[PDB]
Image (cartoon, rainbow, N blue to C red):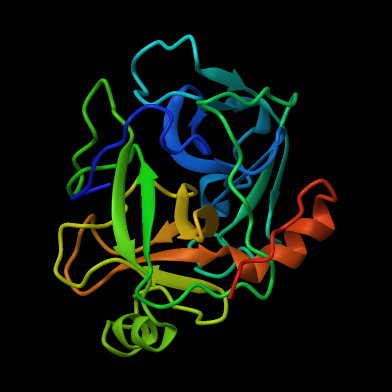
Length: 251
């Protein structure tokens, strides 16, 4: 996260850290006692499920915490539309090997139901332990970063990414993605943040509106970060995981 601030402990208790062979690679969002949603691009086919770990309840990634829990994974289910290096379908369900116990520091975020709409301009928050500037990592002790970003209309994101960007720019799919952020630069999610939550508030409840998916360089100008739009995958999520019940989001 670039341009944001340090969260206080307990603030975003659904945020988790995913490591691969012990190295933090992505975020994710706890959505029940045993399931986490993250980005499919963090789980390439060639990686071994047993080499991942999920750390919950930690605000400083490099500080021991008695409140932190670490779990292995028993299943990884990427969306079947997902193609490596492609934009579509960047979302994956991860099942922890065992259910975890909730606490002040570990609690699930609500999934938005298929028909949920979040108004353009709503200030949502993206969190993570990813880069703080282009190619610059967050320094130890790696305090979780948070950044308020406004949701941007699909028409505008389509303009910014599909019309006003070169052909090698990933394709923005209006039905299944949302961009959120700034054209000004210096405020965005970055490498290492994928899979983490775009948490949007409605009537005092937080919904996983999006999952960090892609964008340009960390904090690049005219390219607000792009997120997988969770509502578009709500029916898929619930059909795969009967335990996960997306919530209807008030008008």
